[PDB]
Length: 369
Length: 73
Image (cartoon, rainbow over all chains, first blue to last red; front, side, top):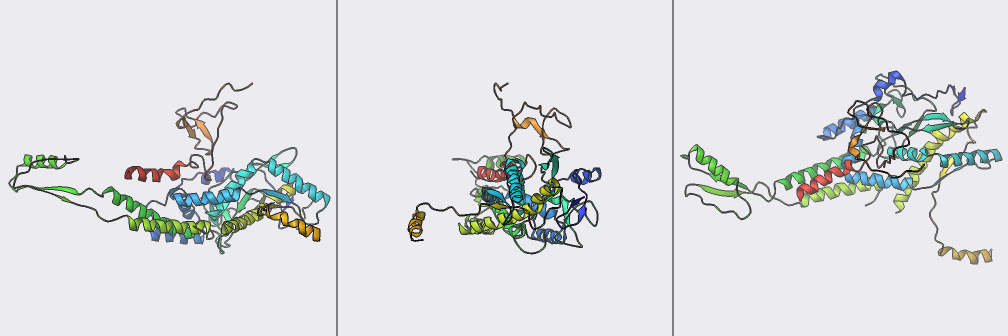
């Protein structure tokens, strides 16, 4: 039996938990769009439900926001590209033995040789907006070595938090208690932007309101622009007019454009009344305020703060990788028990690039000693 | 054995498998499309946003500003 990281023995099954016939029904889902006609009460209810462990409506709302809002998508893409551009290397523990160094370098070489690692990291970046990111693991054989063939992303809406114990995710199976996650078969990465339980640490909680304000303002602005700068044309006719005479007047009113002429009787009158007036200053002011609020929420400014954000979420991702992927590989490949405090980890190249021009000052120091 | 030439194809002639998303198939007026012929296609997809295929393109976010700009102009 394979020994867990916590020290509790268990049985390892290569088949996915989602491949079960009974679970096949819940796998197929229709992606509802709760962003149509958003109401502050509706958003508050969705957030309240997500607090208790629903996590479905909030996930769909976050998906809708990440595609409907251009600024939010741009900022998220910028952040994910910034985190993805870093370089990583596997290093063993301090004062490591020769065998430990050999294992560390072989794992490092394998992970650079693994194509699915980049996709796995990119998919794990989804926990910046959503509260969590869940990916399957497809175990396989490569030269008598247990390695993952590929990792499959899963919809965040298919997971619910345990009411008895929060901060623990479970697979939804239409039951009071969801199915426990299959050990050595999942890659769960969560980003704790704010302290608290899972499902409340995502960026959706703070970004729901500016999105609503900005979208409503822009749609109202577009509607106002539609009926702007074209006054309505009206025509007054005497009470004794024939039914046919009204039709001719109605057709004549509809035929006004460019440099138009026309003759009207003394009894009839024609006037122009504007159906909309105002300026675009308030709509644009609100849109700009919402956009800068979103930019402040995501990036921290409208740089050093970007570097700190990258360091923090890179460290969180490294901890998640060490907890989820590094240990099972060694545990399955090695027959003996894996030491808990002597396992290799992943270190990202989080170092500021030096300036070769200003490091010429080291020569006098080297001469002095 | 080398490829003589590669011919681009209309993206509208492909449909995703309802049983298993993220997999493209050639449309043939059937519930399940024809599976792609091995060693006969060059399929490149850009994952701008995570999720299933057909939702990771730039159309999803660029549809609205295009509408607003064109109607305004």
